[PDB]
Amino acid sequence: ADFTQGADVSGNNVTLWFKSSVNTTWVDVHYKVNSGVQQNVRMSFNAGAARFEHTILTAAQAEIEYFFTYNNGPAYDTTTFTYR
């Protein structure tokens, strides 16, 4: 169930994104910013970049622990990633 993922920055905002190469229909992010309470949010689909996205305001200088849960069409968790 291959995917790619990343964190883009514009301004001070961080956009966690997740790009699927399988039959994915929704994605949630689970994240902690600066070791705070874990947030669980379902992502949006940016057709311009053909990828799922969630933007956090004013977090470019934060540290962010996150992982995705996604379906292949019955869900799957990615390993945990860090944004510096």
Image (spheres, helix red, strand yellow):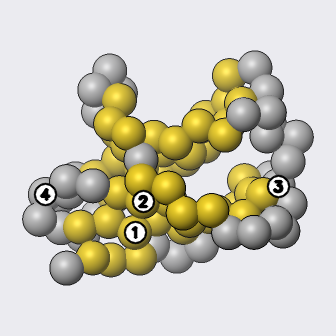
Residue at image position (42%, 53%) is 42
Label 3 sits on a secondary structure element that is: loop
Residue at image position (72%, 64%) is 32
- Three-letter code for the amino acid on which mark 3 is drawn: Glu
Q: Is residue 3 left or right of residue 68?
A: left
Q: Which badge, 2 or 1, comes first in the chain's sequence?
A: 2
Q: Position of residue 62 (x, y in %)?
A: 85, 48
Q: Residues within 10 Å of mark 2 (few under 14, many from 20)?
A: many
Which picture quadrant has residue 77? bottom left
Residue highlighted by disc 1? 69
Q: Residues within 10 Å of mark 3 (few under 14, many from 20)?
A: some
- Three-letter code for the amino acid on which mark 1 is drawn: Thr
Q: Is residue 51 above or below residue 18?
A: above
- Cα–Cα gap, marks 4 and 1: 14 Å
**Residue contact at pointers 4 and 2, CB within 8 angstroms:** no
Residue highlighted by disc 2? 28
Per the rendering, the mark at residue 23 is 4
Which picture quadrant has residue 15? top right
Per the rendering, the mark at residue 33 is none
Per the rendering, the mark at residue 63 is 3
Q: Position of residue 9 (x, y in %)?
A: 67, 30
Q: Which badge, 4 or 2, comes first in the chain's sequence?
A: 4
- Cα–Cα gap, marks 2 and 3: 19 Å
